[PDB]
Length: 480
Ligand SMILES: Nc1ncnc2c1ncn2[C@@H]1O[C@H](COP(=O)(O)OP(=O)(O)NP(=O)(O)O)[C@@H](O)[C@H]1O
Image (cartoon, rainbow, N blue to C red):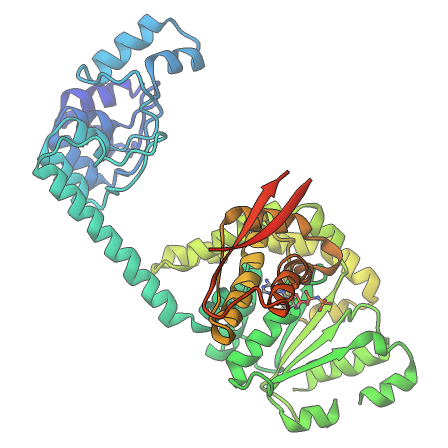
């Protein structure tokens, strides 16, 4: 077939390369053993076709399908001799590693062939000098210490500076989101959804008929209300001012509706951020008034934000939280981009959209009795149980708080390593949520600090270490 395409790529039969290019054949094309044509071309320093391929639009940053002679021989189930003569004659005869070549970009092989020209060609085509192969080796790793290495490392510094400027203006362009991300542990997707919705309304791409309306689905004690207040303080800049919370359970009867119709709280601020808790179990009339608020635009307020919460669909969301995290982090990845493509994949119906219209809305609808009611919401937000790292970070937040307080009041330095956190994480019970952590730290640590300070065993200016001795587990405080 087009084996001759990369035999040409391997021998630099340029007139044939153009030919097949004209027939629309893809440059990314690989061998039966897995190397891209650009790889063979780069390895044998056949620049005319390297140049042409980087012209055609061949991807430089494509990893090799080939691993080792032994390995590929075991995978594709062949004699080691077949595989060997193949890799040797159809690719290169200078490579010595019995290690795996899986994930080597053309830049890798370029450094391995020790030629500056194809390195330069690959770099000019925006190849990654930091792309790691399965081992973790950059092409710089495999570079002889030439000025080739200087070229490649300066490339590294360039790509680095690019990353850094990119960070700087993800900060400049999405400040609310930076604020949420730096004041809230975990819950990536939630922040993304909420912030994006907010500036979606600010820029004017919602029907500015009625203020923002959110529904926070998920579990107790994982950031819902916290996120809400955070948003509030970002908008009104007064921590106190912009925020309203209604405990819905209080309302379950028709007399509660007379009370509900808040009117004064709204009067203090039209523009504030309002939250309802466990909204699923509250009077339908209360919601209809709530929906009337959510449609009307008296009900004076306009530029307000409306948030609702439920433990409803909690179990369902929980049952599978992986594809939600994946999707969330994918969105963050696609956000720091700047071309019409990236936006076009913003067109796509993301798995979350399928997730609302398959499993969630039916349950949401049945509990709610109104098609209209699911219609009224600007956005539905999901909240996830913390992964390990996030729990660690919560504990960390706690210890940092107490260390800080100690250092100002009594000038005491509180210290610890990772094990302490790893142990206190084992004190996280779900039913209370992040506070659970609050408890543990205040129990296993602050009790001890208070006890010691009472007894005058903490002298002003001392230094302490939180340690774990297994003798079953006990946490011990010591003075250094
Ligand atoms: N991601 C989080 N980041 C930081 N603090 C959190 C986080 N999640 C919960 N907390 C802490 O928990 C406290 C409030 O709990 P919170 O998560 O806001 O309640 P909730 O999830 O909305 N459910 P509920 O208990 O009904 O209000 C805050 O003071 C936080 O310090």
